[PDB]
Structures are given as C-alpha cells and as structure tokens.
Image (spheres, rainbow, N blue to C red):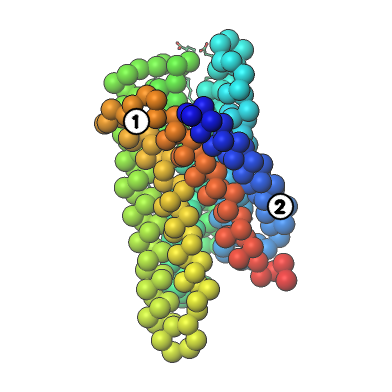
Amino acid sequence: TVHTAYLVLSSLAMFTCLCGMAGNSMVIWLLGFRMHRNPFCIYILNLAAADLLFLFSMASTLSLETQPLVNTTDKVHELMKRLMYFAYTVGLSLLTAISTQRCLSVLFPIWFKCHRPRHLSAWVCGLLWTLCLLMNGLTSSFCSKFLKFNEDRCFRVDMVQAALIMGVLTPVMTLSSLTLFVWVRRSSQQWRRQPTRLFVVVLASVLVFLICSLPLSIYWFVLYWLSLPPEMQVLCFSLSRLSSSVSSSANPVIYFLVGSRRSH
Ligand SMILES: CCCCCCCCCCCCCCCC(=O)O
Ligand SMILES: CCCCCCCCCCCCCCCC(=O)O
Ligand SMILES: CCCCCCCCCCCCCCCC(=O)O
Ligand SMILES: CCCCCCCCCCCCCCCC(=O)O
Ligand SMILES: CCCCCCCCCCCCCCCC(=O)O
Ligand SMILES: CCCCCCCCCCCCCCCC(=O)O
Ligand SMILES: CCCCCCCCCCCCCCCC(=O)O
C-alpha cells in the first residue's frame, strides 16, 4: 500500500544517505588540504562539503519524521528541511560550476592555463555559497510556518527559486557538457584514439544530474501550478528525495575516484 511504498522508499533514502556521508567524508579527508595544485579540486571539495551537508540534513529529517511533530520537534524539523534545501541548491550550483570549468578547460585551454586567476574557484564557490544562503533565507523567511509566513509571497519566492534553478542551472550545465562532448568527439577523437572514457563519464554525469537531482527541483514547481492529489504527493516526494540521495551519494564516485591522479 501507500505506507509500504513510503517506508521502503525512505529506508533506501536513509541507507544511501549514510553511504553518501561516508563517501563525502572520505573525499574531504583525502582531498581537504592536498591535491590543490589541480584547478579542479576546489570545486570538488566544496561539492563534497555541500553533499555531506545535504545528506546529513535529510538523514536527520528522515530520522525525526518517525517521531510525532507537535511541539518539541517540528521546529528543528523545519530548520533541517531548510538546511537540506540550501545544501541541495548549492550542490546544484557547484555541479554547474564544475561542468562549466571542464568545458572552459578545453574550449579555452590557454586562458585556463596561463590566464585563469589562481583563486577563481575559491571566490566562485564563495559567491555560490553566499547567493544560495541569501536565496534560502528568503524562501524560509517567506514560507516557513515559524517566520514571517505568507501565501502570496511563498509562491513568488518559489517561482523565483525554481525558475532560476531549472532555467539557468539546467541549460548552462547541459550545454557546457554537450559542448565539451562535441569538442572532444570532433577536434580530439578524430586524430588520435577516441576517448571513450571521457564520453562515458560526461554522459553519466549529465544523466545522473538530470534524472536524479532535477526531480527534487521540479517537485516544488509541480506542487504549485497544478492540483496534484494529496494521496500521491508523498510518493512524488519520496521519489525526489531518493533521486537526490542517489545523485549526492554517487557524486564522490564520479568526481573523485574518476578524477584521482595524485592518489596513484
Ligand atoms: C543567478 C545566477 C548567476 C550566475 C550563476 C552561474 C553559475 C555557473 C557559472 C559560474 C561557475 C563556473 C565558472 C567557471 C569556472 C572556471 O572555469 O574557473
Ligand atoms: C554573472 C554570471 C557569470 C559569472 C562568471 C564568473 C567567472 C567565470 C569564469 C570566467 C569565464 C570566462 C573565461 C574566459 C573566456 C575567454 O576569454 O575566452
Ligand atoms: C558559508 C560560506 C563560506 C563557504 C566556503 C567558502 C569557500 C571555501 C573554498 C575552499 C577553501 C578555500 C580555498 C582557497 C583556494 C586554495 O586554497 O587553493
Ligand atoms: C545561487 C542561486 C540564486 C541566486 C539569486 C539569489 C536571489 C534570488 C532572488 C530572491 C528573491 C527576490 C524576489 C523579489 C524581491 C523584490 O522584488 O523586492
Ligand atoms: C541573514 C542572512 C540570510 C538571510 C538573508 C535574506 C533576508 C532575510 C529576510 C527577508 C525578509 C525581510 C523582510 C521581512 C518583513 C517582515 O517582517 O514580515
Ligand atoms: C538564516 C536566516 C534567514 C533570515 C531570517 C531572518 C529573521 C526572520 C524573522 C524571524 C521571526 C521569528 C519570530 C516570529 C515568528 C512568527 O511571527 O511567526
Ligand atoms: C538555512 C536557512 C535557515 C533559515 C531559518 C529556518 C528557521 C526555521 C524555524 C526554526 C524554529 C524557529 C523558532 C522561533 C520562531 C517561532 O516561535 O516560531
């Protein structure tokens, strides 16, 4: 029944949350202060931190939804839900940044080598964290039922957040990955041996992004603008949570173990 399909879909989410926390802790330990001559490692460290925050927040959320939410809980529950959302948004922004950096490394290699600011990843990540925190401090301040809660303002701030996420982070990331794919297939695979690994990893990252991370972003959009039945909305929420869980738990595998050159 519905309860069984919720319990099963939440147990998997908790298990993959624990696995993702372990993987991101390993990535932070193995890359926190080293491997930093690489221009690609600052984004990966920040993404690992963001994914660890996401998985910890939503693991706590899933743990404390078993308990009744009346007076003691349901106040930390909202805090950790906003933490989950903020970490999800910053992780999506960091994935877009990683894909754009990879595309620029091959579209403009001279700039990436001898003209890129050496701290550009650092303050790009700082700007992403600051902007995500600011946007989530508006979504929470206008839609949480423990703050200056409103009805006409929640819808506007959500139509800002979801529209920005989808119609900016999806086109930019997918277009950058497609351009990198096309450039490698045309100007690099034609002369020497075809880099099948590059095609495989780019396609896998794009597929994981679109099929796993984006469902949680579009669930907020389809909650409004459409009269979803209240019985099946919990199923959609569970699907979105598990998809984002899988994406965050697999990010260390497809961004660190694949990109492990100093660990050799
Ligand atoms: C409100 C949106 C503002 C714009 C956000 C754009 C996020 C993706 C692009 C910026 C991050 C990556 C920039 C290139 C990184 C690099 O190659 O050094
Ligand atoms: C406001 C949105 C865009 C933010 C862009 C932040 C900086 C991104 C990294 C540098 C992009 C340009 C790279 C060199 C391009 C070139 O000259 O060929
Ligand atoms: C919550 C706001 C702050 C979030 C973190 C800010 C960005 C931190 C970036 C990683 C650590 C600094 C890295 C600087 C560059 C380097 O050491 O090579
Ligand atoms: C990093 C992604 C998000 C980047 C942009 C963050 C801020 C988005 C907009 C916030 C809500 C603004 C709503 C309108 C406010 C007004 O008209 O006064
Ligand atoms: C403190 C940093 C994170 C939050 C930054 C964004 C601004 C938060 C507050 C937004 C609402 C401001 C107006 C409140 C009006 C009211 O009291 O109803
Ligand atoms: C991470 C910080 C985000 C911004 C928060 C700014 C403060 C928003 C207002 C909080 C008011 C709390 C007390 C009144 C609550 C209520 O009237 O419902
Ligand atoms: C990451 C952004 C977090 C923004 C702040 C979220 C706060 C959610 C509510 C927490 C409990 C607030 C309790 C005091 C106000 C009240 O009495 O309702």
Q: Residue at x 39, y 30 (%)?
A: 232
Q: Residue at x 26, y 31 (%)?
A: 225
Q: Secondary structure at mark 2?
A: helix
- Residue 220 in view here: yes
Query: What amino acid type is highlighted by mark number 2?
Result: Met
The percent position of residue 213, horizontal first and vertical second, equals: 46, 47
Label 1, label 2: how many angstroms apart (C-alpha)? Answer: 36 Å
- The foreground one among 232 and 260 is 232
The percent position of residue 216, horizontal first and vertical second, equals: 43, 40
Q: Residue at x 63, y 46 (%)?
A: 20
Query: Which mark is drawn over residue 26?
Result: 2
Residue neighbourhood size for the residue with mark 1, other residues' Cα within 10 Å, grouped as few (<14), some (14–19), many (≥20): some
Q: Is 244 drawn above or below residue 105 in the view shown?
A: above
Q: Quadrant of residue 138?
A: top left
Would residue 190 appear left or right of 246 to someone viewing this image?
Answer: left
- The foreground one among 11 and 97 is 11
- The foreground one among 21 and 246 is 246
Q: Is 14 drawn above or below residue 201 in the view shown?
A: above
The percent position of residue 11, horizontal first and vertical second, equals: 60, 36
- Residue 128 in view here: no
The C terminus sits in image quarter: bottom right
Extreme residue in the top direction: 71
Residue neighbourhood size for the residue with mark 2, other residues' Cα within 10 Å, grouped as few (<14), some (14–19), many (≥20): some
Query: What amino acid type is highlighted by mark number 1?
Result: Leu
Q: Which residue is mark 1?
A: 223
